Image (spheres, rainbow, N blue to C red):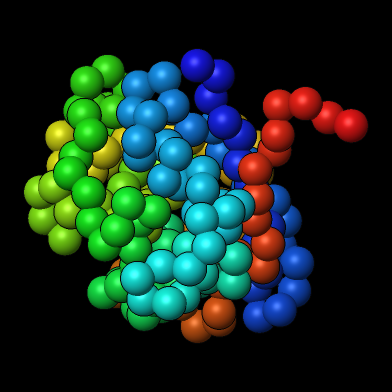
Length: 179
């Protein structure tokens, strides 16, 4: 099965910062890719929370230079929240193959609250993170807009706090067929 492609458009204190395009490894981890894909489009409607199952207007709430960008918390905005399309949380789908190896700058992996607790939160990695191998399910990579990733990364800090709001001002799927 073909790997979906999805996008985020980013704003920093309400200024357009550009586009990040991601490939999702539906070939390796279909359930995890589909969750993330469906959250990019919003097509599943509202969650158990009653908030949209959608990354639109969510924040990158934690950013650490030479490590990662963390987002996907559309219920609490602060790292404690989020929901998958299957409900609150889901099991680790696999650590086989591409799911088991973090690839450095641009690697997409699921954040969690311990083993087998995937939700909606993710890391866009900004450096090598081999210590996450077999802990975070890897489900994609950034294939365009690494410049925008570096732009966001520079606005982080050691603690992870950002001093401007870094927002996914838009998102969606890039459909296979154009018309």
